[PDB]
Each structure stands twice: as C-alpha cells, then as structure tokens.
Length: 496
RNA sequence: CCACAGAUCCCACCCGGGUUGAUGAACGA
Image (tube, rainbow, N blue to C red; front, top):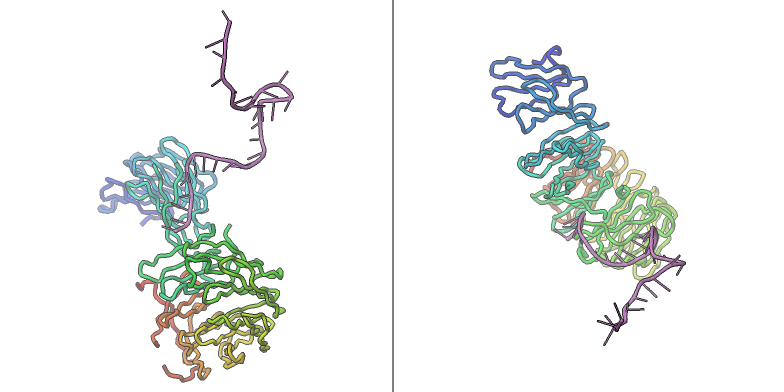
C-alpha cells in the first residue's frame, strides 16, 4: 500500500531492466521502489513539484522517463535518486513516452492535444511533430510506442484509429493504419450483392467502406477540413470501375458529391440543385447511368453519372423533396416531399403521370425495385406503402409511438422492418399490415437495412461507432403483438 | 488500388539580364 505520506496517487507501474524483484511505483508526486519479494520499500524519491502523468523505462541502466502535466520530460536515475536531464515541451500535456531502439537515440512524446513529437536525445533538438494525428476531444494520443528494434511507431487514441508511422533511411512517413468512425454512423448502405462491403457515413464527416468478411478490413473514402457531414447517401454496384457510382448530399450544401467505389475516392462530378436549394435527397438508377437530386426548394434534377451533365429537371414539389426513386426498368420515377405530395413521373418523357396528397409531411422513402412497392415515413408516425404501378396507397402501418428513424423491405417484399425514437424495431407483414414482431432496445436504432439477400440485417444506433449485424433466422406466424415485445441487447463485440 | 515521394517540365509571378545589348552569325597585326 502506498499511504499518502509515502507518496501520491499511483500513476504507473514499471519494471526497469536488471531490477530483480523490484517494482517501480510512480505516483503523481514521487517515485517509489518496492522489493516485492521482501515487501520492503527500498527507495522513495524527493517530492516532484509538478504532477507526473506518464512514465517509461529508458533503454539504459537505472533510468526512467517521467512526463508531467507541464510539458516536461524528466530523465530520472532510480539508483542515485536524482534528475539527469529535463526536456521542456512548451504548453503541452504529455500523454505518452517511448524510446526508439533501432540505433537512433530518439524519444517520442505523445500529447493530449493529439500531437506526436519526435526529439533527438543526442542532438538535443526537436526532430519533428506529427500534428493532430488523433482527435483531442477523444483524449488525443492515448498511446504511442516504437516497436522494438524497428523504425516504426504505433499510435492510437480514443477516436477509433490505430496508425503506424515509419522513419525511412527525415520526417516520419505514414505507413498503414486501421480504423472506423469516431462518432456513430449516420447513414449506411450495402455496397454490393455479394455481401462484401458496406458504405457508411458518420457525423465525424467521414465516408468509410467496411468489409463484412473475416479480415474485418476497412478503408476511409479519400476526399482528395473534411467535407460537411453527409445527410443522404446512395450507391449502385452496376457501374463500379466504369464511372462514379456513389452520390452523397452534404449538410447545408446546394450540390451533391460523387464518389468512386473502385478507387475508394471522391469522384469528378458535383450535382447542383439549380434552384438554389440544399440537397435533401439523392438516388440512383439500377443501371448506374443516372443520378437523382432532390432540392429543399422542390426541384428534382437528373444527371448523367458518366459525363456529369444535367439531363432533366422536374418541378412539382413546393417544399423539400425528401425522397426520390426509379423503377428497375427506368419507366416511372417517384418522389415525396414535406408538402405531403407523392409525385409520379414518366422517365422517358417528362410528363407528370400523377400526384397523391397524403395527410402528413413525408420524411423518407424506400423503394423496393423487385416488387415496385415503396414505403414512406410520415410525421403522423405511420408508414405508408404505395404501389408504383397503380399509383395507389396499398397499406398503412400504425404502431410506433415516436418519430420513425428508418425502415427497409425484406428482399422478397413480404416484410417491412422499421425503427423509431420509441426505442423499438418492428417487423410488419404486408399482406395483413400487422406487426408480427417487436424488439425493445436500450440503444435507439437510427438505421435498419436488409442485406440484398435476406440473410442479414444491419442496424446503426445512437451510441456506438460500429454497425450491428443481425441474423435473420426466419428465412413465421402472422399473429399480432402489443407489449409482448422482446427486450433484446445489441450483439456482442466478442463474436467472430 | 490508392497514398506519398521523386525529379523534370513548364507554367506565372519573383530576381537579375536588360534600353549602357538577347540572338545566332566561317579568323588570321
């Protein structure tokens, strides 16, 4: 036990080389040496004026490096009990220390602001500083370690990333890294029909592709200070490699961006609304030839994904267009808006084929291409299912007690699964319109998507950086439910 | 596959040239 007279609050436990049976206990105020075999406190250093936050054994005898709340790294001799050296890092709070051990006498100093500083111990000069490699709001650099005998330093923070930096035989060069979002995913989509990749956007302003396979590989989409946060997303696998196959809408921007799934990078085109409105909805044809953009001012624009050229423009809605889609045969185009209007248009000409007026503002659309049904989420907490061929409402789903966050069709077309602020995930059988299953979660689902094949369900939630995968073990009764809902927990991070 | 480098190239500024010559131009105290 370290009583408060013996030392302060324990910060770190270290074992120095050749210190047989002797544990070094560094506290906020001093450094102790205990013989763990005999129990004897064999050493206690003088009081340290400034709070010690970090400690790290040096690659030479008797020396331990100590970081302080003030940007000081102190080389301390445990045998003689005195300072040997004190390096000052101006106005930084040290969070990690590591010595290079490949021949070069270098020291790395991580900080809470997310900087990684490299210092030459022999030339007594600052070698370099990797600025903002990890987010400060997530603790900055929480750990940075030179690999033993190698010119490689591994770094990490609370921003869900693990980076590796090298020193070529010169400033350090980015080598490789792995990561995900630092904030919960806001929008997701399955990228392909082989269940390989998922496209995922977050409020951390990033666009990522995550593999669904065992290697758990992932890669951020290159934006070559980030683009504003994504507010709508669409992707089609048809033209991968040939031209742009991803469209994103960004917060408070009057144009949509395009991306290339093959090269995992932003694409060539930007698609303007043309009516000075923000982009509120985006969509793509199944063939991959066309991009659709819905404006906050009501306009709908159709662009050519190959050349980037504006093809067609429609003006029906007088409020924000919240959803757009086109049938698999590119015959009939459908739209929805906050004005509660459902628009039906002929794609080959530009004729208004029809209009529906619903009783509440419409916030989102999901179109089922294999059944030509599309569902709409309304502000009155209902889900309206419409047949695109007949241009008629065929079903209306009532049950949710709060705002609907997301929904999707089961691949066959038999089911619709929906999520809400009411912290439920419900399954609706379309032939009856009744809720046949309900799940209560403790972490509200913000997205729900069926895999192209009926096997998996992907969900995103209010808290958590990742995407939850569920197995659809019903590939069932038509009995209605009420408070017989299941209170299920999210999948384990220990699986697979 | 991207990333990043590389050097080149310009490219335009920038400087000097330069209004007290840029150019190329085949010898014979």
